[PDB]
Structure formats: C-alpha cells, structure tokens
Amino acid sequence: SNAMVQKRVQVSLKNGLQARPAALFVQEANRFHADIFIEKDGKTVNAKSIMGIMSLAIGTGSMITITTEGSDAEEALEALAAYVQ
C-alpha cells in the first residue's frame, strides 16, 4: 500500500505543456517536497524533469495523469492540476 494521490486532468494550455509553460511547470514541481509524476498515453515521467516532460509532447487538450506521493503530495497535485487546467 501507498499514500499516493492522482488525478486525470485536461490540459487546456494553448502551448500545451511545452515551451515556457513547460519550464515554469517544472520549476513549480521542483518547489514541492513530494515526488511527482506525469503520465500521458501510457508513458510516465518525473514532473521535475524538463526533458521528461518535453518527451511526452503534451499538446492542448491532452489528458494527463498527475501522481504525487510525499509530505505535500495533495498540495503539489492540486497546484499542478490548477496550473494546466
């Protein structure tokens, strides 16, 4: 068992999670203590990795799953979901 939390969210950003929005997302992810992952189309990356995020090619309208686990997991999850939604 584990204490992870996850949500499936629709990315409504016009640039998708690419370009400057991706860089600021990764900066924001890096502020949290929790481990944070993003999954798109079955591929999962560490949200604190820009090269991982870019590798997902997250375009506008994409559904992604955000997963977190750690001391501030729920805060991290909700902040990142509110960033992209």
Image (tube, helix red, strand yellow):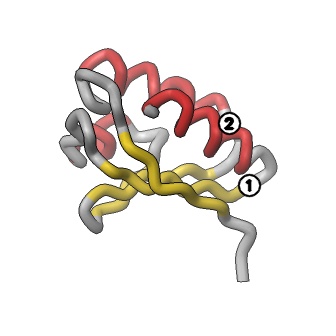
Residue at image position (25%, 62%) is: 41
Residues at discs 2 and 1 in contact (Cβ within 8 Å): yes
| Residue reaching furthest to the right | 71
User: How far from the left and from the top, in percent, is residue 21?
Assistant: 35, 20
| Residue reaching furthest to the top | 20
The residue that disc 2 covers is 32
* C-alpha span from label 2 to label 1: 9 Å
Q: Quadrant location of the N terminus?
A: bottom right
The residue lying toward the viewer, choosing from 13 and 74, is 13
Are there few (<14), some (14-19), or many (20+) residues within 10 Å of tag 2? some
- Residue 68 vs 26, above or below: the answer is below
- The residue type indicated by label 1 comes to Gly
- The residue type indicated by label 2 comes to Phe
Q: Earlier in the sequence, mark 2 or mark 1?
A: 2
Are there few (<14), some (14-19), or many (20+) residues within 10 Å of tag 1? some
- Left or right of 78? Residue 1 is right
Residue at image position (72%, 48%) is: 74
User: How far from the left and from the top, in percent, is residue 5?
Assistant: 65, 61
Q: Tag on residue 70?
A: 1
- Left or right of 29? Residue 84 is left
| Residue reaching furthest to the bottom | 1
User: How far from the left and from the top, in percent, is residue 11?
Assistant: 36, 37
Q: How many marks?
A: 2
Q: What element carries label 2?
A: loop
Q: Tag on residue 61?
A: none
